[PDB]
Amino acid sequence: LDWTTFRRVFLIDDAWRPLMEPELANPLTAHLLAEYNRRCQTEEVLPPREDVFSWTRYCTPDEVRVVIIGQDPYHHPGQAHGLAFSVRANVPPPPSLRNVLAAVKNCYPEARMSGHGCLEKWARDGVLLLNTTLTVKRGAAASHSRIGWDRFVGGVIRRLAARRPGLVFMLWGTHAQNAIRPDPRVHCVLKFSHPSPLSKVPFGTCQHFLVANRYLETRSISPIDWSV
Image (cartoon, rainbow, N blue to C red):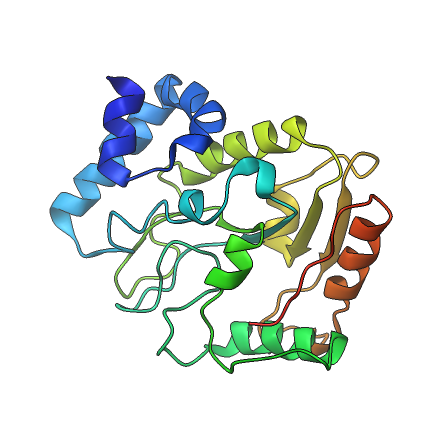
């Protein structure tokens, strides 16, 4: 029971099986898994185990329209919940996320912004919010960056992109842009500087949300309601 067992430990939705099962078999994956489990033995690991793969539960691969790439989970307890950038509902949007939500509003002023930072509505709408590193040691940013999550995540994104052409990729910042390099002739690849206020260009100027909807429409795919 390799897939059966794996899926039980992380509570993964079965619709992702075709995309993830091939990875289970890679010997590099076993090292990754054992290392994640060793860390859990010796430190406070976030997000909680049943949240690590929450993104498999919001929508299926065939429902995915946009892919937004992040780095690693928020390192303070109570913030991260398995999605890149998103925080639990009663957690005030941190700096980078505020800039994202600011950009959406500039792009779509008729947007119903709730003022919250939980992006579950987006996730259910086929916006895949995927971090390249899926866990972090409490308080230490980037502490799990070399254990192997990115090879595994990249593997899943490669299989998703091949399964369906015409995806929109939103690569913000140097790391996201160096980690995932989709065929720009087959998918819509949108690049911008990192959303943090420390970037030279203010993220609120980003118009990726507009351009994305313009691409989807020319493909007869329905556009996203970026309200959240």
